[PDB]
Image (tube, rainbow, N blue to C red; front, side, top):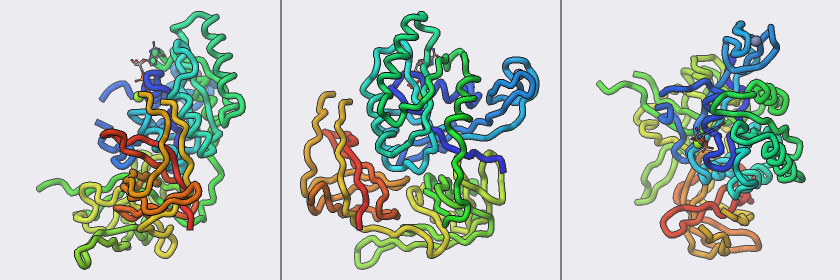
Length: 396
Ligand SMILES: Nc1nc2c(ncn2[C@@H]2O[C@H](COP(=O)(O)OP(=O)(O)O)[C@@H](O)[C@H]2O)c(=O)[nH]1
Ligand SMILES: [Mg+2]
Ligand SMILES: [Zn+2]
């Protein structure tokens, strides 16, 4: 198919223009769509078709060239991940780096550099090793030539030594759509579709689950991101942790098997789906089991080829600096503390039952399906709001 091939994360300090840039690239000026956004992770996908004008040779995301008017040729479909707040974004990168193939760091030319949030976003990208970065120097029309060049130097200084050191800095105006063609061109040159092994065991992280049968039948539907291999109609799949049940007054989870009846990607039904963008998986599952996002956070794969399920985790801990109302200093993790953990699209509270050298043991409220070595975002309830304090690496 012509489904999205890569997911591009939109990062940068609040108000610098991430959302406006996303809309400028996706062509959305109306409308909501936030009804397909994640619940465990407030993540949203917005596709755009990258095309090139045979005539003037400039890139754009319209079937009609904005510069000469001619019809453009299809090059590749991509998906942009844009989230509401700083926290949700940071958590998304640390919990699911496998969801991003590259990133566009938005930096507003009229703001003093660098800002706390921008610093934390780069830190997250540094931690997950995401180096396919493009920098968008936004709101360029709001500063004179001198300010503009000076801001550029600060950015170059700012990115030196980081995973963004080799990133191009592109002066643009997201709001007025200025110099956007250069940015689209950069997406093609700096965020190439990775060479994935379509033969690795399939793995999909479930974002949302529904019962699409109108009020007043088709099986349950799972919406998510394929991070490995591929899915095909007719495929038999296993879902973990699975369906919850009660045994001796306690909750347990039963992995469940089903079959793929349909696949929606890129805005249409297909026979095979791959990594990139959101994928809708129609199954033979009883809608009663997927209704109301009951399977959000679960992992999909082929029977006998899924990561293990954990009731508790031994985590190698790496606490964050954190510079973004005072309370910057992250206090050490104490036994008995209740933390909020995000791993992949799964989310669960955890009770610290043991402490070790740069390590904690945590009993989970809800089991999670993950592989040893996977990254887990750790949040602490500060007053009355969960705050990201670091991440852990699952150990055996
Ligand atoms: N003048 C100007 N304003 C812009 C530009 N891009 C975005 N904005 C505005 O600045 C504000 C913050 O933008 P928003 O897209 O919500 O960015 P976000 O907070 O990073 O996700 C909005 O009022 C936008 O209309 C630009 O190129 N020029
Ligand atoms: Mg925004
Ligand atoms: Zn053209």
